[PDB]
Image (spheres, rainbow, N blue to C red):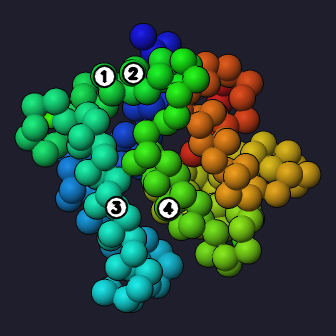
Amino acid sequence: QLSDFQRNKILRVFNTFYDCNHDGVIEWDDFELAIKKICNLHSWPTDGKKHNEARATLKLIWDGLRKYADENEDEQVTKEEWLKMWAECVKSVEKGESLPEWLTKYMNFMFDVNDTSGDNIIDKHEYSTVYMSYGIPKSDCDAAFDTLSDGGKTMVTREIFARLWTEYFVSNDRGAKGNHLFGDLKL
Ligand SMILES: [Ca+2]
Ligand SMILES: [Ca+2]
Ligand SMILES: [Ca+2]
């Protein structure tokens, strides 16, 4: 099974990042709210291009996640269904396999949502602008970002972000840089 460390990293992403309306389950409703929060954050127009593409990509993510995790087909994913699914993805990745396509889509969507300047690099102000809207404090965004970029030695490109992403969800190493991808963790 998942270690405490892995389980707790996985539950945080559930509670802090996927369950937008904080009712304790993930549903299409949570994706609709995520889109409005991003529109408000970055001032995107409703039914404009950015808005429409985000909606189309989020449907595909929700569809993948529902197919993977929604055991009882009630169109809602509970924390139990999430962890049940995650325990398999982690073993799966450990046996040389990919992470699910919906999860890779969500990783690329988030990189895009961070990199507002479109230069293929997340900078520290862009990183804190997104993560703060999820309730991550400024000091924990800056500490995470110092770790993720090696104190500015490493440019946090799409590919670097991708590798750090996989590390967050699957690593049981308390030293892995990707542990901090969603805000500084005290370990
Ligand atoms: Ca919810
Ligand atoms: Ca369900
Ligand atoms: Ca940028």
Number of callouts: 4
Above/below status of 166 relative to 108:
above
Q: Of the residues shown, which amino acid type is indicated by label 4? A: Phe
Measure the alpha-carbon separation of dots 3 and 1. Answer: 22 Å
The answer to which image quadrant residue 118 occupies is: bottom right
Looking at the image, is mark 2 or mark 1 nearer the viewer? 2
Residue 124's label in the rendered image is none
Q: Secondary structure at mark 2?
A: helix
**Label located before the other in sequence (1 or 4):** 1
Check whether the beta carbons of the residues at disc 1 and disc 4 lie within 8 A of each other. no
Check whether the beta carbons of the residues at disc 2 and disc 4 lie within 8 A of each other. no
**Label located before the other in sequence (3 or 1):** 3
Check whether the beta carbons of the residues at disc 3 and disc 4 lie within 8 A of each other. yes
**Label located before the other in sequence (2 or 3):** 3
The residue depicted at 20 percent of the width and 50 percent of the height is 27
The residue depicted at 70 percent of the width and 45 percent of the height is 144
Q: Secondary structure at mark 1?
A: helix
Determine which residue is flagged by label 4.
109
Q: Of the residues shown, which amino acid type is indicated by label 1? A: Lys
Measure the alpha-carbon separation of dots 2 and 1. Answer: 7 Å
Determine which residue is flagged by label 3.
58
Determine which residue is flagged by label 2.
88
Determine which residue is flagged by label 1.
84
Measure the alpha-carbon separation of dots 1 and 4. Answer: 24 Å
In which quadrant is the N terminus drawn? top left
